[PDB]
Image 1 (cartoon, rainbow, N blue to C red):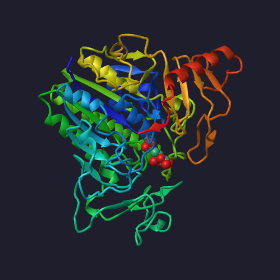
Image 2: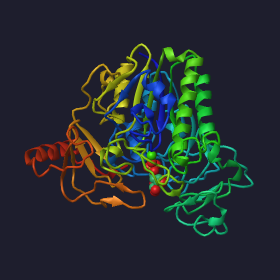
Image 3: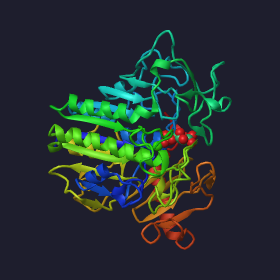
Image 4: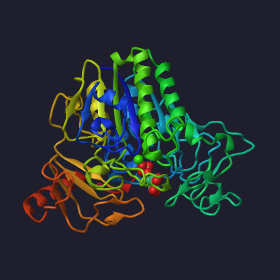
Length: 487
Ligand SMILES: O=S(=O)(O)OC[C@H]1O[C@@H](O)[C@H](O)[C@@H](O)[C@H]1O
Ligand SMILES: [Ca+2]
């Protein structure tokens, strides 16, 4: 098997945010098309409940929590994945695929954080760790620098107006969302009150690069355009395309063709904008007859958040829409909604269409699963936590992983066998008011029967001492002593 592999990888899109998992409160027709065209997963997880660790886990096949510095990265964060590492991109390139990444990166660029010259080539970047083509946002939509990077170079730079970036202090004379809120077309709810770009304040300060600044209205359009351009450009030979959307992540600034259309304000409108992007990819493959020999994978980097730092009506217009489906918590949390994400695999003539799998799966296993598919032996040390299971990911086998370690925003761990879930005691608040999410951090051990109690309402650690011991021990077995070590 040497098929094309296309990831459509969403940001902050929860189990109940797409209509494929049963929601009647939003209509995502293209995502339903994909589901009825392949296999839909009800128990597939991101490695982490935040972006940078989930993305690190996926491309490296290593649990993010094994390394300090794999947490939510700043725009000016240095390359977390160094060229010495064997990457999923490397696997494909070495197997003779063309490789491209389009959209959100959020794994750092350049050598030393806060010291990059954004007017010069970023070294090292995406093109040093197995990607032949890159068209990326440095970090998230709400983080400076708000420019696009093509093959590790910022595009549309006027050298008479060079970019500067600091997360330490403002450049004197540059206004902020905090001090100059009259310059804003969208107001912050918490943080997001530093440098201004197209009337929206961000996290971090910048100056110059006016010509290189993106427009948030046209991000979905620009990224999806480059994604389709890349599929059209490589229609003759095997390619791996990692298409990672801005969509559902703040600031939520959908194309005018989507403003108002969901009734749930910008947040809902950006789910429809995501569904549009999915449409563009599926149609490009169908136009070119690429649906004969293409594996399409749709998923999210982590669970959902309603208010994630802007006054964008997300709370007021949610109605009875449940982003996390029936599952407790959301983004940042130890609870299921933090990591249990929409996941579809579609592969014509391999995967039975309209199929469902309750297998315990994780995005960390794709690396090893693609080695199994390509029938190639992984180098010593590569994808160390990645468990191969092509049979499970193609819906031909009920049984997924036997054990899975999940991580939250405070880097506390949980372990599950698909049925029981043990949350290891750790530091951190029980609740974040700003984001209105239960984080699941506790000094007390927690045990939940996800089959009898999927809402994780009823902690039964006390009533199952022998089971708590078995699963505490199993967690540490998988941790080794390799937790929070240096990059
Ligand atoms: O998905 S993530 O990229 O990990 O999100 C990172 C988050 O950091 C937090 O400081 C903000 O409240 C969020 O708005 C978002 O920027
Ligand atoms: Ca995210």
